[PDB]
Image (cartoon, coloured by chain):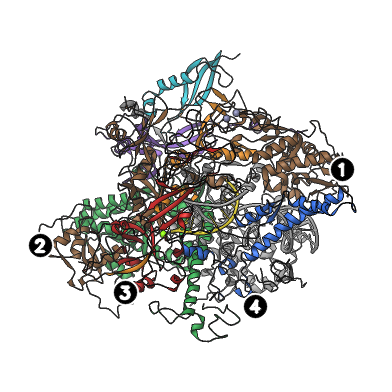
Chain colours: A purple, B cyan, D green, E red, G blue, I orange, J brown, K yellow
Amino acid sequence: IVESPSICEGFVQASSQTLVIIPDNERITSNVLTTFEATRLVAVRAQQLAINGSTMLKKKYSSPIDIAKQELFNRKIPLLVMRCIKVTPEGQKIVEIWNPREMGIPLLD
Amino acid sequence: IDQKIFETTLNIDDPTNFCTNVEAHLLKELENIYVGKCFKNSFILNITGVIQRSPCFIMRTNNSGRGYMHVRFSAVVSYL
Amino acid sequence: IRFNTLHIHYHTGNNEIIRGEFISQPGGAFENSSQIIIRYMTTGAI
Amino acid sequence: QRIQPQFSFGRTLVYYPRFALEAQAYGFICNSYIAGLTSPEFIFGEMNGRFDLINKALSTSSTGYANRKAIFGLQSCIVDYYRRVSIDTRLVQQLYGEDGLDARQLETVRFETIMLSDQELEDKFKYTGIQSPLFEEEFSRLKKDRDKYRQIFLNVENFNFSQLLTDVRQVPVNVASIVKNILLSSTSGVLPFDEKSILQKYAMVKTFCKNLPYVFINNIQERLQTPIPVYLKRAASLMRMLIRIELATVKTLNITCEQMSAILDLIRLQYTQSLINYGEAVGILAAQSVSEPLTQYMLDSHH
Amino acid sequence: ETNQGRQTGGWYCFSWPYRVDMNRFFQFYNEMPLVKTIAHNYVIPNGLNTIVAYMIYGGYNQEDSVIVSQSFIDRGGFAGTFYREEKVELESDIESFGKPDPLITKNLKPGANYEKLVDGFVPVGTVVKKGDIIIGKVAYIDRSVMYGFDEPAVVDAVMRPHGPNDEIFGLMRLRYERNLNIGDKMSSRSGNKGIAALALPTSDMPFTEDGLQPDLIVNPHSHPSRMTNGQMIET
Amino acid sequence: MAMQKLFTYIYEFIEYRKMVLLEEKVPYDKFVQMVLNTGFFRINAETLNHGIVSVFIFGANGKYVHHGGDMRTLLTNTLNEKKHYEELILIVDKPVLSKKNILDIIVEQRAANPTIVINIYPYHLFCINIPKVSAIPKHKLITQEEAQEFLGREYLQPQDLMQISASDPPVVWLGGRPGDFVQIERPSETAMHAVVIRFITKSKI
Amino acid sequence: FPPTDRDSYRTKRVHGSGVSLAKAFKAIFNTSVIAPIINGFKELLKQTAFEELTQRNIIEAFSAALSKNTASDLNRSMEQSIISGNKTIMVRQRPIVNRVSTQSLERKNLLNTISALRTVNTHNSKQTERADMMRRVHASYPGY
Amino acid sequence: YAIKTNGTNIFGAMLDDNIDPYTIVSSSIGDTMELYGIEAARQKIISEIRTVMGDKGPNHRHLLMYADLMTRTGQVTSLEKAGLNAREPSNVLLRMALSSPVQVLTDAAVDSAVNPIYGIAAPTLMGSVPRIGTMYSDIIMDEKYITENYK
Amino acid sequence: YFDAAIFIGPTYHQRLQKFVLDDRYAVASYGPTDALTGQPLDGKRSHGGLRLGEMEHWVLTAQGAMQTIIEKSHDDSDGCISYICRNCGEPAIYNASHPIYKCMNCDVQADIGMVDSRRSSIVFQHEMRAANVNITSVLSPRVFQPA
Amino acid sequence: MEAGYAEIAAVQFNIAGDNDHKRQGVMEVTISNLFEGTLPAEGGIYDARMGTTDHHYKCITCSHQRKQCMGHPGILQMHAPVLQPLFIAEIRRWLRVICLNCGAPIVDLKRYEHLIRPKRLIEAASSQTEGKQCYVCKAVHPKIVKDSEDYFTFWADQQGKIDKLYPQIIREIFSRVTYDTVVKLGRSKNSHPEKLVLKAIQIPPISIRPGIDINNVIQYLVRKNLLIPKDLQIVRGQKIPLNIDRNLQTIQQLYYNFLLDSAPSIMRRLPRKEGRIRKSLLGSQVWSISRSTICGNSDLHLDEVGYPISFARTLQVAETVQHYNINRLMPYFLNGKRQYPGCSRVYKQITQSVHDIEGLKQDFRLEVGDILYRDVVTGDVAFFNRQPSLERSSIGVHRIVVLENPKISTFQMNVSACAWYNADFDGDQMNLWVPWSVMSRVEAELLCSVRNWFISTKSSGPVNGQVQDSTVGSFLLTRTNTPMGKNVMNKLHAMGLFQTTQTDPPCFANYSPTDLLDGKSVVSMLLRQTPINYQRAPTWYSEVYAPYMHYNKQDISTQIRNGELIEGVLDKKA
RNA sequence: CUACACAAA
DNA sequence: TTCGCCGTTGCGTATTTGTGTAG
DNA sequence: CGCAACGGCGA
Ligand SMILES: [Mg+2]
Ligand SMILES: [Zn+2]
Ligand SMILES: [Zn+2]
Ligand SMILES: [Zn+2]
């Protein structure tokens, strides 16, 4: 006789992955930030300036959005952009890490 | 009492200040969360040290601005 | 629709070519009305 | 078609006899609105207006169902980091729009060499001011670009019903406009003859065209001069050909070398700003942009 | 126009003061059209003979907008009374009408006024606004009725009629003084809808050499595509 | 007619596949009378790797395309000769493509001879020079090394590419087998021609 | 001959109030008077003999089924047929279709009231030929 | 001068010797696919959608998107349920969101379907947010920069 | 004076009973919510609502917005926090204040993850589970940069 | 223990069996009573262990106050097994594929090996399998005929001897099936047919059946399950009493009506436009949003929307108080709800509680980490939306301009902005919501601003321009001749043309009051700020009017050279 | 909440 | 024996707004 | 109202 076990018992969750960072000279993605990427960088920075308060902006701004926009424009943003290229099925997450402070900023205005 | 490797994803409510000293803050947070409580068939006495971690990814599914970071760490546990 | 009148319909494909619907009222507006349907099927049967 | 005889057998309205032959019986209105239509003319006009209202009423539901189905069939198409379009990981396009460009960053410019004959191609674009084989190969490149454009779009004409060849194309950068603006803002005037300057300008335009497919990758691989994929080389074909047409020697005689350097960097900047963004839901954009003219196709059905 | 001619404000009923009607608008002033039709021999005309200037005036009447005279609004042009009703049943002997006692209560409304109540009802003529409580029903479980509307109202009529079981209920009538506001829809008899976009004082409105000035300024661009020549001829 | 076009374009197909003929090209009258009498016309060609490709052109009314027994017998006898037999190309009328008896015969003969490729095609696939059709962009097979380097640069798996049937007319004229890659130069009204690479999947039928 | 023009008013009739309320009354009456009283008479003739009951016994059985549980539901049923307009209403543990269609008298103005009382309703897809054709100005409309 | 026929018989026209067989244009996508292949069928889809669009049509890249979506598998798939089943059989949530959620759910349950969360409908139906747009690329904190600057 | 003579005269005009004071609506971040989905109620009559429909989500997705889909559809809607075990894929029981850390499935080997979801999606998954369809959420694997 | 941040990567769908229900269930339903006083009856279908729908009690299971409680399932041990309503067709397919005596696959299993796995079982059940001889036990397979009355009753017409296939019999038949048969039939291990018969069903969480009509069905099923004897056993051809037969049929029909009826079912909430998916998941009802009639405002920029002040005091912007913005946020806090611009709520960091400003007289202290909800002010970004949202520009971000007139309650916009939304001012209503989060505000400003939709994503061309009054006004201004003569104005009127342009006015110092300026001169003075080259015939010049009229030569060829309108009129073409 | 009706774009 | 046919079932038929009415 | 599986019975 057969009595079906629960689905959870036959469920193996997943293999944890290792971050494979593509070397800088082997990156093939754009060195210019997309409008999506620049917008997300400014949004994350502004929300973090809403929860924190520390910035490297000599000029004082009364809005976190202004501080974050100037940090992105003045190449002082403390964030990095990670572009996940491939998910190898041996357990490898292949990414390209891009520095926004060295990237081309889109028009955004 | 023996060393056991644990896997966890933390939550980082101030990612800017956390990243000023990632190792120290990570050890403090791990000791705070997993101090003398059962976790995965083990009592874990104290954190020996982190053996592998992740970049502090910013949370994507909420507008909180927080980061999480995955940390795989070693610790000594009290199995009976 | 007007009663005691025939409503021929070239309705459409379901093995029915044409139908004729007649609703008959004994002579008032409140008397029971019985409807007859006179189908003409593709098989030839009326 | 005219007003069909719907009133009775052979009758359009109670006002017109059976099998009437006059044009007014079938919806011909001899009056203007200012003159004021008669009663049957107003009935026919009301028939027309009601038909238009019904069309507007039902096209909404039909086009809405079509739009929802298209959205759900297309929404999974998202631009990835290679600017391909993929569903999850399965490729739908090798490059978005086959050129990797945002639809909001396109200008319609004319390709001058397309309709030019062999003689007028020499007269307008073959530069005879320096007895060099560099300009011979430049003119050969221009002629070959024209021939390739002609062959491709003549084939496109062949496998279509009435899709005529045109010399106007949507491109990310209007090179002619950039050259004209730099000419206008130039402090100097008619440049004196300078063989070194002309040769250097030709060489730098050739190098820029050779490195043009690197806008699709980055400046790192351009600096390292790594191989470019074939599809990326094809994606830059139209802009390469336009740059060769507009930045030819004959049209850039009065352009200084630093002015041409400014022109090339402006072109590259405008090209970089025209590429589709990573993660754009281009399937939803396509669904919206194709569903909008479906409403007008339904509305124009009665024509 | 057939559609718009039936939503036009006017004397919606001749016996309106004896009716507790809901969402009903009684417009004070009505005029016979200067160019009437036979329909006005059998039905009352709703509307006014506004002076309309077909002109471009600052681009505030484009795309079916209309510029109105603020003075024409102030004088009663299209002004009227909007009516709402509040009928609340007493269910059974458990519930009754009276001001709830805050000490006992059960479910007193937070932020509510609960004042302005006499014998359980707000008296006639009292302005009610947002959180004010109208008709205090108590079962003591609080079952009062809160106003809620963002537009203040004046209690027009209160009564306690006997339902079809010899039981009393509420049905108070609320009154709104509705002048012609910016954003109110106007239309001509030719079907030309318009939203009031700008109200100008009498000194800002254009005037003819003999002093005639419009009530509404209608864009000439509303005509050529819509072909509403009847309105033009009527003018 | 279908027979005349087939006769004039099957050798164009053979030469486009870079094959050399093993017999002499008979006149058209002899070809059609042989199809009517024997029931099929056999053409044998030699590939660059000395493999043998047999092209069977079956007549519309022949006995081999409506009785599965004769088709089984013919396939078994032709697959038992001492030849390399890189591929067997069976050409039938389009209605024969829907006959489950003949299709099942082809399936069992393929299973019994895994090394040999057996394909059954309709008449219209060889009734015209397929690569010369204006509507068909230029297909070309790329080697597994070039495909591997393309996929490695793109971080792609072969299953992530757009797919093309091995029974696709341009792929048939190319000779691409399932698992291969075909590069396509398609005209573009946005970019003035573009290059795409498609993964060849199992042939329909 | 052509088929029957489904939109022509040659073969159409407008029934309002009279016919509609009459049919509703017939349906409700057959369920709320005749059938209650039939059940009452069956009960009376079952749990009582015959040829011995007086004339008043029949009258008492008659009024038993009509002075109890009656005139408060048939009246209610007709009121429900007037108000609302949902297809089926409950009449003594059995539902019957509501054959009368009513709309609230919205007193936007006198013209709206008159037009609402002059509206002919055709209460029964959107992309068929029928859906387009039955919304058209038919050639039989003029004057009616 | 050419001949515009009613009905598509591409094969019959190629058999005819009085018309050019290499420039036969047929308005039907099925005949083009059966006779010419998937690339010619994709071009036919582009041409037919462009014909339907009219004078004021969209940019060509949207027609390209339509034609490449429908021909990505090597066969012409539709924008109906069947096309979604062919192109995204495992995307149970998207197919449920389109139509017939109970039938799709039943088939997913018996089929033991695994649904990777991608696109728009699948993340949305799980209360999540699509990984597109501003959230296509994930942001990580610059530990080196913050350590050396945000003391 | 205008250079052009202006056509001016009495044109009978009607005030249609569509009042902006009735039509206008503005709601704040709080109000009555649905018991089932946890979403705001429907419209002005219920004192809370206004719907961002399917097409609005399509438009915000085409714009690539997000973070506005997040705000509107989660923060200003029934957005909630789900807990998944990461070891069985089933919903877990987590409570920070009163300490509960468990899943009815594998107990000692519970790894509860904090998953941002909506109450509508939780109800949807509960309804698929009520129809005897087991929904197991795989959860993204943890990634580690090499030691 | 700080449940870490996670995202769902994949979702797997499986058939839930008795073991799944037993493991996942937090209670077993035993008693049919609903309530025990003010608290739900323990052991009933409303038991708090399965969630809380009221705020009077917590969940016991998770101790969450309704909003944070997602609900938990409970088991109902059924005295008689039931079939799974969702998989009746699967039960039917599995029944006419295996022998009902040993669970053997009496089917050419080797025949179905080339097929794709989902179609394998359907094809196998499409075979004859009637009167077929078995192999392991050598028995004749009866004909399984689906009952014509209900959706869940099966018969075994064995040579005319019809017998009911009760779900217990079906459970035994399916239990005899090996995993090898299920694998070779194209199903999975988790799709064994034994799962298709439910001994213990799952009582759904109270979160999905709140309010004390679907609960009536569950209560009916529970109370009718109590009637079945606990140890009822049925074998093939038992011929059980009619009473038990009616009870079993009613229980199974109750389960079928609970899951798949049409009270609305669990599965009937999913489909249709107003179902769970399309109404609750693919769309949403949202807070902090406004709607009003739109009217025209010529003095608003194309990227500006007029917001009535009453709506600006309803919708709020969440401003987290920090050192850099405390001085700017101080006026908002001090104004409160009394004067504009003010605020409505303050979130206290050290309290984790919001406080209304009207009741916040005793706080008067803003701390870093506090969240102030202030009124919408001029310059804020807002999302403007018109339905139906067909285009990418149907939702755009405009700069808020607050109309401080209390008599205005319309959403005013420039007439040239109407092309984004396909709007006009004949009664159209538009949704407007002001982003309050920092992330949404950043992205509204940087990504969804209406400057990004000036060029159509559809046609790649411009969307906005002069419409109606402005098109004919441009023509009138730039036309060469008026009926009064040359189209010239003196210096005062040339200056007055720029009064409301709202940019830096040009210089007229070189023009005397007596000087006359053409319309093209002032147009060029405007267009010089952004010099462009334009050369095209105007819409004014048509060949259908050429035989008539007298077209001025300077009007029928519009030319702009570096911002100078050399000649020609400006109209719809330009 | 489930109809239904009247309306708006 | 492999397919057409044919009832027979389900599924689906623009979006967002208001007001009622009743159950 | 239409569309499409479907699955059982005629070929
Ligand atoms: Mg409008
Ligand atoms: Zn678990
Ligand atoms: Zn709970
Ligand atoms: Zn057996």
Residue D51 is left or right of residue J427, and the answer is right
Image position of D46 (left or right of J572): right
Q: Nearer the viewer, residue J69 or H83?
A: J69
For badge 3, the amino acid type reads Ser
* Residue sitting nearer the eye, F70 or I52: I52
* Residue linked to disc 2: J513
Q: Earlier in the sequence, mark 2 or mark 1?
A: 1
Circle 3 sits on which residue?
A: J542
Determine the secondary structure under disc 1: loop
Q: Is mark 2 within 8 Å of ligand 1?
A: no
Q: Amino acid at mark 4?
A: Pro
How much space separates mark 3 and mark 2, taking CA atoms? 37 Å
Question: Which tag is nearer the camera, tag 3 or tag 2?
Answer: 2
Q: Residue furthest bottom?
A: D21
Task: Name the amino acid, label 2.
Answer: Pro
Instruction: Estimate the spatial distance between the alpha carbons at disc 2 and disc 1, rounded to whole Å.
Output: 116 Å
Q: Is mark 1 within 8 Å of ligand 4?
A: yes
Residue, disc 4: G2
